[PDB]
Image (cartoon, rainbow, N blue to C red):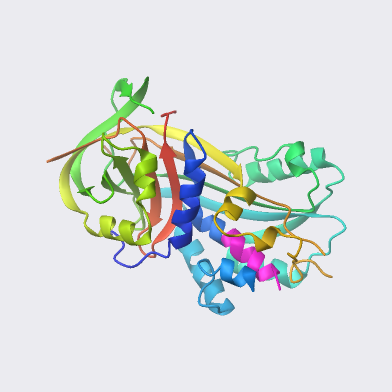
């Protein structure tokens, strides 16, 4: 279990993360990989502009390859055992008047771990409740709400993704009696955890940020932290992150002895994805032209797309020189190091737990 040695297919992921982060002053967490599942589901559903617009998401213009890729990354990622708990769940909530094609339900289920169910948008109050109950059910109450009755106004089809994670570190932190200290947001106190250890690390002059990898148990996942240098901000570091620059910055990381101080955090984040998607070039699927002939028996389209993600880091593992002191805002992400998947991406502006 070492860092990924391949080339990440993260051109879309990074574009999307940046667009979300630029428009929120708060903590954020989301799943770029899962957003790619949603777009591929809509692609599978559709009849071009759509194909040019999704070229960073679809695998080599071949549907069999696209299906096996997403299926493989999904099965690699997901797990519920002593080492970590990661569940991804996806649903289309479809108005009653729409006839859902059963074969679409089968490919959705099989390759994308997604489902479809009927609701009545004539009753946005009951429908909100239905969606929110689905969210609780599929995250074991970790997430509980994602929509209000108002956010369904005028809707015919709503696509919802939820994801949550908690794992054991390979190298746990000591549990310390209120290790409370200042956090300098863009001040407050936070609970920190601190250890010395051997961790992949670098100070990246190109990014203007330190990077730290902390692995999770299970030989698959790690959390990366990108901490801007004191003269720098998260937004300025983002402006210099693209697939090439990030690939190189991670490539330069070597195992070092590092003194690591991190704020504990636990929070969730949700957003309606229509707008950020359109901002990054994905527009056709939301236009008067869009259609879903392979999903709905024949003229309808996806009204709204929502994602809600939840995340927790704390000290815990199974048991038990550089300075990495994360006492100001930073970026984090979780990747599957066997395949390069960007499962979670987020930022901390205000530690909370």
**Residue 9 visible in image:** yes
* Among the 4 quarters of the image, the one containing residue 2: bottom left
Q: Is residue 315 left or right of residue 195?
A: right
At x 65% / y 40%, what residue is drawn?
A: 146
Q: Please, is residue 194 above or below residue 332 in the view?
A: above
Residue 264 is covered by the magenta coloring: no
> The N terminus appears in which quarter of the rendering?
bottom left
Residue 41 is covered by the magenta coloring: yes
Q: Is residue 114 left or right of residue 193?
A: right
Count of numbered badges drawn on the protein: 0
Please tell me which residue lies in front, 248 or 106: 248
Q: Is residue 4 left or right of residue 344?
A: left
Q: Please, is residue 343 above or below residue 272 in the view?
A: below
Please tell me which residue lies in front, 276 or 271: 276
What x and y, as percent, mark residue 191? Answer: 35, 25
What x and y, as percent, mark residue 251? Answer: 25, 60
At x 28% / y 25%, what residue is drawn?
A: 176
Magenta stretch, overall SS:
helix
**Residue 85 visible in image:** no
What x and y, as percent, mark residue 15? Answer: 47, 55
> The C terminus appears in which quarter of the rendering?
top left
Q: Which residues are magenta?
A: 37-47
Please tell me which residue lies in front, 106 or 242: 242
Q: Please, is residue 118 above or below residue 270 in the view?
A: below
What x and y, as percent, mark residue 55? Answer: 53, 70
- Spot the residue most to the left: 321
């Amino acid at each position: 279990h070492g860092p990924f040695q391949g080339q990440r297919q993260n051109e879309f992921d990074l574009m999307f993360v940046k667009e979300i982060f630029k428009n929120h002053n708060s903590n954020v967490v989301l799943s770029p990989f899962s957003v790619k599942i949603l777009l591929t589901l809509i692609y599978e559903a559709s009849d071009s502009n759509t194909k040019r617009e999704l070229s960073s998401v679809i695998q080599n213009d071949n549907i069999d390859h696209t299906r096996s890729y997403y299926k493989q990354l999904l099965e690699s990622a997901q797990q519920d055992n002593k080492d970590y708990d990661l569940n991804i769940a996806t649903n289309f909530f479809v108005d009653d008047f729409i006839e859902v094609i059963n074969k679409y339900q089968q490919i959705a289920n099989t390759h994308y771990h997604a489902m479809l169910e009927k609701v009545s948008y004539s009753n946005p109050t009951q429908t909100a409740a239905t969606i929110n109950n689905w969210v609780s059910e599929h995250t074991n109450g970790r997430l509980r709400e994602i929509v209000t009755p108002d956010s369904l106004e005028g809707a015919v089809i709503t696509l919802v993704n939820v994801i949550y994670f908690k794992g054991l570190w390979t190298y746990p932190f000591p549990e310390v009696a209120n290790n409370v200290k200042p956090f300098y947001g863009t001040p407050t106190n936070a609970q920190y955890m601190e250890q010395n250890g051997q961790f992949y690390y670098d100070n990246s002059a190109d990014l203007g940020a330190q990077i730290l990898r902390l692995p999770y148990r299970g030989n698959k996942l790690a959390m990366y932290f990108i901490l801007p240098n004191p003269d720098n901000t998260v937004n300025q570091v983002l402006d210099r992150i693209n697939s090439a620059s990030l690939h190189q910055a991670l490539w330069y990381m070597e195992e070092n002895e590092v003194n690591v101080t991190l704020p504990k955090f636990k929070f969730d984040f949700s957003e309606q994805l229509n707008e950020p998607l359109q901002q990054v070039g994905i527009r056709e699927i939301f236009s008067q032209n869009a259609s879903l002939p392979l999903l709905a028996r024949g003229e309808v389209r996806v009204s709204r797309i929502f994602q809600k993600a939840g995340i927790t880091i704390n000290e815990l593992g199974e048991e038990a020189v550089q300075i990495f002191n994360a006492n100001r805002p930073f970026i984090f992400f979780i990747e599957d190091e066997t395949l390069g998947t960007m499962l979670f991406a987020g930022k901390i502006e205000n530690p909370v737990f």
